[PDB]
Amino acid sequence: RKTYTLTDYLKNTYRLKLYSLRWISDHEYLYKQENNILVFNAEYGNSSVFLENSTFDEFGHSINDYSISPDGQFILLEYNYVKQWRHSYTASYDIYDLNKRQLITEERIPNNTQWVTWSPVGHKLAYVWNNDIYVKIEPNLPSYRITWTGKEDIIYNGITDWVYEEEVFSAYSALWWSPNGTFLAYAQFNDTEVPLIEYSFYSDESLQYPKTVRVPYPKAGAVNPTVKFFVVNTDSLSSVTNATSIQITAPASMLIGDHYLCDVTWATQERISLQWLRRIQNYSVMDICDYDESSGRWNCLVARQHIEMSTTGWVGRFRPSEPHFTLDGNSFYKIISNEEGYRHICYFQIDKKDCTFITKGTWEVIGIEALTSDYLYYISNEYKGMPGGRNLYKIQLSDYTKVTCLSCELNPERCQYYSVSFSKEAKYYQLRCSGPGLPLYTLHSSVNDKGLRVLEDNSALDKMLQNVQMPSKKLDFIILNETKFWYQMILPPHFDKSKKYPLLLDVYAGPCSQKADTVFRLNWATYLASTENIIVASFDGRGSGYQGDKIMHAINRRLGTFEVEDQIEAARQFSKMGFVDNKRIAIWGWSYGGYVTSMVLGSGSGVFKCGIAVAPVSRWEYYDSVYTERYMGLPTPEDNLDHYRNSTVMSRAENFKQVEYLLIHGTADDNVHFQQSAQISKALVDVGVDFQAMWYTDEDHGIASSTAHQHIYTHMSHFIKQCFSLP
Amino acid sequence: RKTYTLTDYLKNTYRLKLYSLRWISDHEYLYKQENNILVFNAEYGNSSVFLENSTFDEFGHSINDYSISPDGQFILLEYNYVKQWRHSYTASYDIYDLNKRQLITEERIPNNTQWVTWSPVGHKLAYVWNNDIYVKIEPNLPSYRITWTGKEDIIYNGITDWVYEEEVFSAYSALWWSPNGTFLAYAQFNDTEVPLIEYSFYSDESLQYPKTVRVPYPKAGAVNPTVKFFVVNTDSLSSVTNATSIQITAPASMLIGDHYLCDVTWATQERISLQWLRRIQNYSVMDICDYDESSGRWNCLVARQHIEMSTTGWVGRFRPSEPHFTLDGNSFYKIISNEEGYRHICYFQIDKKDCTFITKGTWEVIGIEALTSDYLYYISNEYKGMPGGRNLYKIQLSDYTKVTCLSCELNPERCQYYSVSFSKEAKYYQLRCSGPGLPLYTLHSSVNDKGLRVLEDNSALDKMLQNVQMPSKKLDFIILNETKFWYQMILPPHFDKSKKYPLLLDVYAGPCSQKADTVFRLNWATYLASTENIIVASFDGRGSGYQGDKIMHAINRRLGTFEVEDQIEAARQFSKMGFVDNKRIAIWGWSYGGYVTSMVLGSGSGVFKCGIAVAPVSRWEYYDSVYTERYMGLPTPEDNLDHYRNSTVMSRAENFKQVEYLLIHGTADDNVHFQQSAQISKALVDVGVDFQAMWYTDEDHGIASSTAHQHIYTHMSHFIKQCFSLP
Ligand SMILES: *[C@@H]1O[C@H](CO)[C@@H](O[C@@H]2O[C@H](CO)[C@@H](O)[C@H](O)[C@H]2NC(C)=O)[C@H](O)[C@H]1NC(C)=O
Ligand SMILES: *[C@@H]1O[C@H](CO)[C@@H](O[C@@H]2O[C@H](CO)[C@@H](O)[C@H](O)[C@H]2NC(C)=O)[C@H](O)[C@H]1NC(C)=O
Ligand SMILES: Cc1ccc(-c2c(CN)c(CC(C)C)nc(C)c2C(=O)O)cc1
Ligand SMILES: Cc1ccc(-c2c(CN)c(CC(C)C)nc(C)c2C(=O)O)cc1
Ligand SMILES: *[C@@H]1O[C@H](CO)[C@@H](O)[C@H](O)[C@H]1NC(C)=O
Ligand SMILES: *[C@@H]1O[C@H](CO)[C@@H](O)[C@H](O)[C@H]1NC(C)=O
Ligand SMILES: *[C@@H]1O[C@H](CO)[C@@H](O)[C@H](O)[C@H]1NC(C)=O
Ligand SMILES: *[C@@H]1O[C@H](CO)[C@@H](O)[C@H](O)[C@H]1NC(C)=O
């Protein structure tokens, strides 16, 4: 009879089995068994082996990822993985012919390649190297040289810079092929005047002098990257003339000032859609641009432009959403907030100024997952009115009121969080279920939506978790000015409502965040509840997502206000329930959570004994322009400087005398710079408040190193245990 | 009923009075009584007015410092002080005609000036601005520019670079006037190929992007600054034809490569002495150079050369000793290591190389303080064979056996640590007594060694310390391996040795250090004994100074060995004394003391429960060449690399699992770089040992900001109380 220990969490004793497959046709997907990678047939299942691992063991180098070509002829191996930022990395690449049975040696892909992608059909390659774009019409051929202007830290061709990577595209890649892989669309970013963030990287103890890393990084109000857009034709590449890309200029109302490229989506072989966002991110335009054969140019007609804007806030959850065109390319679906401020699927005609909505209600559509000619498939939180649940729906295109829930009723107790993966023409789908019970992976046919087999139900984990004393998750709401607000609690085993438990408040609370859901987790909180008998709770107040614009846009231009006040009020609500020890309530968070934590601790509320802030923001002038300005506008006297000034944690320094505070930050944090914490510490020293700090040499925003990760949770555990007088 | 508290220490409740005087001649001096400046006399006794704050009230700026021309016709005012390194700073200056107290309005000295000085007689002015040397013959006349090669962070004319400032000269100036003010000697430094240490500077929270500070700084082994030495004739300075500076080169045996200028000392109006130290600091040379009148040149004869070398260690305490010259210039005295390790005064004939010792015995002369044609005055630790005492000895130059202690018998019980300040021809002298009693300042006639008067006796401070329960101070020795090793103890008031006290070991242990002496102090240790009833102890083990080369050279090429061992053995010996709590012994230290504390905590000896390291060295390769190499040699396969690698705190990480460790470091430490501590924390993370940490944003090696100084000492108090379970 024993608990889920810290060493359990940290060491990964109770492992969570996944089921990762890559569709490659309408009928088949690839998946790993004994490392020997196989292929399954969705119809019956004569799942014969595809690529035995007695192939690449004494190939010479460590395999990291691979990529099968669409036509199925060439596996693209990947080694020398060297991570950059959250998405970016560099690596070495070699190709392996299946039909010739061997690996290619001439016209090899350079070391230090920045990104690689196959065409969507066939086997063409496109790769970025040294900031320039290259294309290989055949793997064994010499590449064609698409761009000549790439320059380390200044001109990026076909890859994003820091801020486009982290904030706009969530990808290092910036190449998009057309469907039949004829045209290659790419973006080029210019960082010329984007000031640099500089910081030290101490490296191995063998490095005598520290290295100063320098990254183009626009802090709020700074000069932003500019952006241009190009399309080249890959079927007519010459070796005796430089291939000439065609520029598609942003629409007029974008060129009038600073703007971003926020979406690229091909609709047909000869039609592409670009979405642009103004720097003041409440106005955005979609351009449909058609290819003209008799000139070789692209034409975005004025009348095909669609405008999406917001008077209450910004546009989209984080950016405008992506269109989903019909086969013929004359219409699209995309999620937009309606008149009521709730996000729903709207159906657009290229020619018309106005769309008709095909979903509605006090819930939101999370995403469009597949569009056939008979049915639209989407994910929502409609079921049981739980904004923290996810389910698969299909809309009958011939009568959109006829909607079906595919996943709702499959396993009601076990499963209320779902995501889907469709076959190439959506004839089959894999259903992934992430809680409340053990995760569950299942396969299904689109014909009857009949369940075919269980892929992975984590019975392995179940069978050995039975004799661990597990905490229960409770998920509920409280009320506030006639509005529902949701929370979750990880409750210790044998929870007794007549005992006063100490309480940790797990906060993130950034705009569109959601901490109160039905996902099952084995994390630090599990340890605190299982081992230490600490109620760890999380709460979604104002600014939180997936419940409508009224709640989401409540912190518009006013960060460090309602989302902070609301965490404090949540605590008062939790004391008022009488199973909480008033004398032992704490708060912690990472990233935006670190900022809210810090603001709550400096609030003078008196509700919180102590807290921990990991890589927090300290004032918004220190964070990147694209995120920050979305919610804060510009930091100038003409826009929002006053509130930038009023929302710093530094200005609350004196009130840290009222709490025990632990501040942790990594030194190699490229994202929220160590600066932010340096300024916190300095302000606390200046008003004479005592507190604890911990820096993590060379660690980044996730402090993800194995040893660093273990060290930090061990440090926070000790701090909380001593904060709560735990033995 | 009350004790000396942490606030008493931080807010300076009980101040030590000083009698800081400066001699203007051989009869009179100055003193800051009130804050108005007064002239004083010792001749007939009287003392009149001279200056005040309202002489320079409507001035505007607050005066940081002043300086009278030797003749007393001019006063130089120092304001706009901006500190740089340990001695270097920049400032703005104004000159008054001290006769008329009116400012010299035109041809003013430039802002941002890096050093300024009067000639030894008359009123000549030499200053350095933008790394170039300037001379003002009459304060209202235009300057003459001496050098034209000054370039920031690259060529330094008349001022030191980082390492010459910290380690060689302990000064910013590299300018030296001749006794009558005709010649201005100076040094030029070239840091062209010297690598930069780089680190972030965060500044006020207004600074959106942190600043990167770049300092030329040779770590152990790196390329060093080169040097040149010049003299220029400040009388024949024209106005139409650039000044020509005569170069005195280093002797041959130095130019074989990599050497330093470590002493510059004039002998007459036309004779100057230079001392050069090979980069391997066990071989030094002295060159004596005569000005050739029918040439304008300086000639240094090979016969006149003398050589200071050491077969068992380096030469000097931290540098070759300075020479004091008899009036004719044909004779000089300088302290060197005698035949059997002890440091004593040697008498030199300029022409021949066989010197002869005027003192001997198992004690050391600390410094030669005054020279007349009659006697020679010096300070030493002979009295009662106490390494940690200082007294003033006078030796008869005609008969070396007839020596007299001028300070020994004055106040035996109160006063065992003297320093002296002579008048410009040694007819009068001040005695500073720094302990063991309350400091006492007394003026004497040297002509008959009669005590004239008590200047300051600290009877004010004596008065209030009777209302306070003050700690006692024990100074004694222990015999280890038939050798006397000295220690000091700060013992709680009402100390009773049938109790078991917790004991903090206060450590520095650096080469030639002394933490065991007769000096009275009011510091953190005073509070710990007085209030927290903690014994604070220090111990001078192998490597400490002022007890003979045997003891001091004991760790040559062997940092992190015997000085680490001996601190551990000190604790054992203290616990074996029977009034220490074995379960509660802590260790702490700053800078080199930080390094030792850490090595001791890493040693696995099990004696220490916990410890604090502040700005420690973590491995010797990171620290500056001049200091490190002297003790370690080069970190190369053919010299002493093995020991460099054997003596890092990183390698001892595993052993910190036995102790509570607090590691503190300022992020703007130009001296001991944050790196060193970043490598400590990373090592400890990587083996998985928990520890406390604290950075100080923008503090240097001193962590000397008012607020930070308060913050750190408060933080360290909490750590020690808690480690000791003090309530
Ligand atoms: C990247 O953008 C910069 C502007 O920030 C461009 O640099 C300018 O180039 C024009 C050429 O007409 C010059 O007149 C300017 O002097 C340049 N400005 C600066 C500040 O350098 C540059 O054209 C862009 N680079 C590319 C290849 O698109
Ligand atoms: C400082 O020293 C550097 C060498 O470390 C000197 O630089 C050289 O100067 C010569 C003569 O002008 C050049 O031809 C070399 O190419 C330079 N080498 C390097 C590495 O820069 C410099 O001249 C010195 N300055 C002074 C005033 O002494
Ligand atoms: C101050 C701060 C710092 C980081 C983030 C963040 C962002 C945005 N940079 C994004 C990209 C979004 C597109 C999801 N992801 C994550 C996981 C995080 C996060 O680690 O929380 C948000 C705020
Ligand atoms: C690792 C380290 C760091 C600094 C020092 C130091 C030195 C030498 N740089 C000197 C210059 C000497 C002439 C005394 N002074 C002092 C006060 C200190 C010190 O702060 O203790 C010695 C070792
Ligand atoms: C890449 O690196 C490997 C090993 O360093 C080398 O053999 C290969 O030729 C390189 N390829 C290219 C094209 O740079
Ligand atoms: C393509 O353009 C680059 C840069 O303008 C030029 O140097 C090169 O000659 C061109 N390539 C060929 C082979 O035509
Ligand atoms: C020093 O600088 C200030 C401010 O720029 C200026 O007004 C003053 O005249 C300067 N003084 C000298 C000595 O040049
Ligand atoms: C002195 O020499 C410098 C630098 O070599 C030169 O620029 C200048 O012309 C000379 N100055 C005068 C005042 O003659």
Image: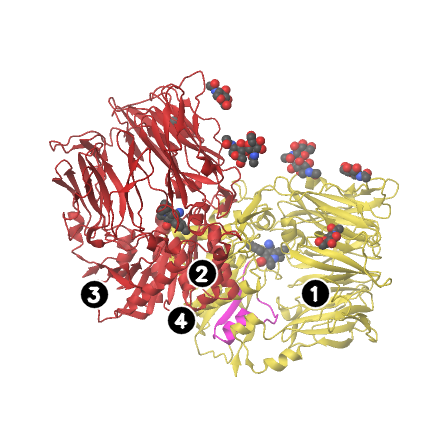
Chain colours: A yellow, B red
- As helix, strand or loop, the secondary structure at mark 1 comes to strand
**Real-space CA distance between mark 3 and mark 2, rounded to the nearest whole angstrom:** 38 Å
**Real-space CA distance between mark 1 and mark 3, rounded to the nearest whole angstrom:** 76 Å
Q: Is residue B430 magenta?
A: no
Chain containing the residue with disc 4? A
Disc nearer the start of the sequence (2/1) = 1
Disc nearer the start of the sequence (4/2) = 2
Q: Horizontal placement of A460 versus B260: left or right?
A: right
Tell me the magenta residue range. Answer: A516-542
Q: Is residue A540 magenta?
A: yes
Residue B282 x %, y %: 41, 46
Residue B102 x %, y %: 28, 22
Residue A662 numbered mark, or none: 2
- As helix, strand or loop, the secondary structure at mark 2 comes to strand
Q: Is disc 1 in the same subunit as disc 4?
A: yes
In the rendered image of this protein, does residue B126 appear above or below residue B586? above
Residue A482: tell me if it is visible: no
Write down the residue under mark 4: A725
Which residue: 14% across, 47% down? B410
What amino acid type should be assigned to the residue bearing mark 2?
A: Leu
Give A248 or A102, whichever is nearer the viewer.
A102
Q: Closer to the observer: label 1 or label 3?
A: 3
- As helix, strand or loop, the secondary structure at mark 4 comes to loop
**Real-space CA distance between mark 4 and mark 2, rounded to the nearest whole angstrom:** 16 Å
**Real-space CA distance between mark 3 and mark 4, rounded to the nearest whole angstrom:** 34 Å
Chain containing the residue with disc 3? B
Give B366 or B141, whichever is nearer the viewer.
B366
Residue B222 numbered mark, or none: none
Residue A379 numbered mark, or none: 1
Q: Closer to the observer: label 3 or label 4?
A: 3
Write down the residue under mark 3: B495
